[PDB]
Image (cartoon, rainbow over all chains, first blue to last red):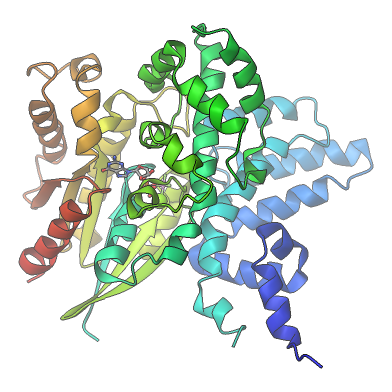
Length: 134
Length: 314
Ligand SMILES: Nc1nc2c(ncn2[C@@H]2O[C@H](COP(=O)(O)OP(=O)(O)O)[C@@H](O)[C@H]2O)c(=O)[nH]1
Ligand code: ALF
Ligand SMILES: [Mg+2]
């Protein structure tokens, strides 16, 4: 038989791609711990808040939830303001006045991107991640 | 075990993360052939992203293509999701080579200050054959040239024999700046980067605000902070190489009307910029150490590090 260690395999899977990482509950948690040491966890919080906002059924809930999310992550001076460009910010504001399930697609994309190209590769070189391999 | 903390600060796109890469090359573990393969996809993505910007700018600015066949290429290239890009093949290679060659796109590029376009565009676009090669392996210079936006605050230790340097890289956009407080403690020294070439540009973060006015305001703020009264301050006026090019076509006086020096003269221009910065705190007698830098030039950055360590921190 060929031995494979369950934790070694799990952790390795996280390095296949960022989208794989995000579908591993323990991947997300390891990554979140990492973001917090870089003070960039608002990127992941925002992203998660969008995935959840896509699940909404009631139109009533949708409207006010879009406002919460915008006030929280998107607007200039927002308490957890995510690093995005003026256009994406403003396109989001327009979307907000007739809110739908796609309201944050553009912004969620930029943030996804931000994490994927910057934080994720560094996490894969972190001692915290590497210790889980040996 | 003797250890010093150094901040890299500056607005977005000043060259902070490029400094870190150079530390890694000069004093860290460098870039192996395998490391360089990890940058391949990003190179591809920077190329697509840059061409997409120019394509949308063609419309926004109302510049016509000179060659009709290039419209079809633009449709093709615009439809790409850059996130899912992992190879660089025809028809995409030839579309992009062909688009880059259109005098229309070249006008658009010459007018890049009126929208947002990443600085390494020309460097990649002039070398697409090298990059297209089925078995392309990024050079160290390709790696230094790649654009990846930084978010958060990150510490890179580097062992120079005599001392450890704890370098801190930070995101430079407005929203990122609220986090800087987390690295402001026990700072030996600050390396403040400004893009010499950013005089005619506007911020990505906001609507039509000059990028250099922004760096001034930021520099002024940093200098006045009393917890930095005993930290040495080094102002790197970076991207001096891009300045050499841009100064021939974009006049400094059109952005800073106080500039009374000659046109098309990089040296006078950069001296004026330096002067503007040094003149922000007339009431402070604190020292500013400066140097004109090119962050993508290893030799240039090697010197700048030896001098900080050998002169300023001893
Ligand atoms: N030609 C040239 N390119 C530079 C210089 N400094 C930075 N760059 C490039 O400019 C872009 C942004 O630099 P980066 O270090 O990512 O900015 P920051 O970390 O946001 O300050 C990258 O593509 C770098 O390769 C320079 O002095 N000369
Ligand atoms: F714009 Al940056 F690090 F300040 F990518
Ligand atoms: Mg950076």
